[PDB]
Image (cartoon, rainbow over all chains, first blue to last red; front, top):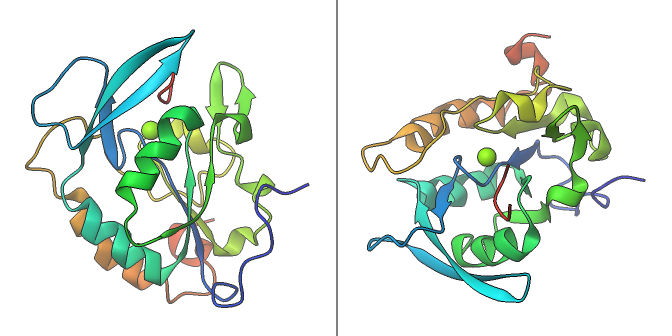
Length: 180
Length: 5
Ligand SMILES: [Mg+2]
């Protein structure tokens, strides 16, 4: 069946927004970095590796606002043993109603696709914020593209997107504004 | 790969 259960009472009337993790909200690496925001131990083949995570500028303000404007859902092509701890440390305000990982993506011709139709929401009221266009090849008309982030601390894309999301949260059909 | 491919 569907990836998500019915939307909770207070969320039922909100637009559902799937938010990507890597290169969208944070950037991680196995190469030690002094200014990492999070260091997370990830076990692979019995060996514990340390992953250094950097937060994208304004992500906290971004997640807090989005959390109250939409029914936010984390959808990533990364493994839970990596992404679950990051989301635990990152999402302080419980903006994420659900979290979906690699196993929930559809592997289609070399790419892990975020197939929005498996979500179980009315696509007229669903949006995806992902840095990789290949992620939403099945629903390019629900996409609110955002540039890939790695470490540019001068980035302000998340901050500047809020006005747009503020407007979308009001419409009753995202296609009406996203062309479809 | 643990992160997004
Ligand atoms: Mg990504």
